[PDB]
Image (tube, rainbow, N blue to C red):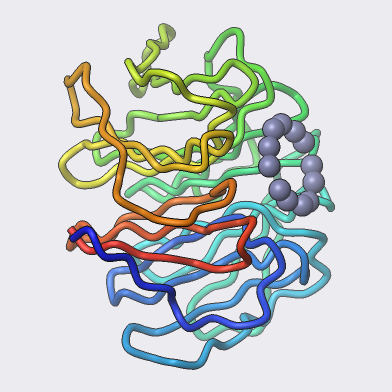
Length: 251
Ligand SMILES: [Zn+2]
Ligand SMILES: [Zn+2]
Ligand SMILES: [Zn+2]
Ligand SMILES: [Zn+2]
Ligand SMILES: [Zn+2]
Ligand SMILES: [Zn+2]
Ligand SMILES: [Zn+2]
Ligand SMILES: [Zn+2]
Ligand SMILES: [Zn+2]
Ligand SMILES: [Zn+2]
Ligand SMILES: [Zn+2]
Ligand SMILES: [Zn+2]
């Protein structure tokens, strides 16, 4: 599609992250209101998730069981909420400096861009032993995504680039995006196409796996977009941060 639609959220203050579950429910970190909201497919009325004590949340992810993971940026922590629960859990990450993005793989491992420590960390489900991924030369990373094979994709915000690291490899590569300006969000779909919010250029770009040729998605009117998600139908959801709204484009 080349016709975007604005999702019927309301009252957002510079939304920062977005995720979409297998039922098409859309989850958004409403950064400036210290809360996370969600909208079921077809619904015209959001609900607020029962997280507590959030300071300007920044990334969100949802797993196949509907558990919602949120980077509680201002409290240097990552929290999660199981489907139907009213009681969040704080994951046992330590030493985080204003975490930004979060991703969760098919094994339930949770990956966090530890923005202010220039690194990416992960915790296997149920573990309290965090691991620092062997990326090198990052500068305040901002988004993270993980594909079906466990390959990790990171927006290396301060270096205007996107890097990738296969599970068990110690050697990252740089994806051949071009002309990015402080990219923020990243998502990877089931085809391995990588989507990036090119924050400083007010646009969203994508790169098919193994291609050297990015394309610009036909969104309109974006103002410093911040997060991107892609559902199983290939619909692309973007937090249009500077316009206080979430937009989507069908495949
Ligand atoms: Zn902002
Ligand atoms: Zn802000
Ligand atoms: Zn902020
Ligand atoms: Zn901040
Ligand atoms: Zn910050
Ligand atoms: Zn920062
Ligand atoms: Zn920063
Ligand atoms: Zn920055
Ligand atoms: Zn920046
Ligand atoms: Zn910026
Ligand atoms: Zn900005
Ligand atoms: Zn901003």
